[PDB]
Length: 49
Length: 50
Image (cartoon, rainbow over all chains, first blue to last red; front, top):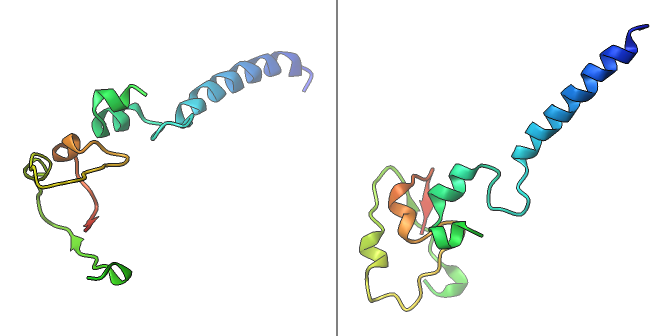
């Protein structure tokens, strides 16, 4: 618990990467979070949006 | 059926060309939602209900 400064510097960088990866599961208002769904379900004219 | 009492048909365990449908001049309307009408030949479904 005395090395909490160094272990927190490791934790904050791990939480920043884990947050950056979990945001790939978000829809952002698209039909799917997974890009191969959109490109396998829709024409390019529709999929571009 | 009358539209107050619409039929539902389970479609399952079979293969379906949709181009025989979407190429036909018969259809006065042919909307699709969440999928392209053209793309249906490239996909599978758990069941379909007509």
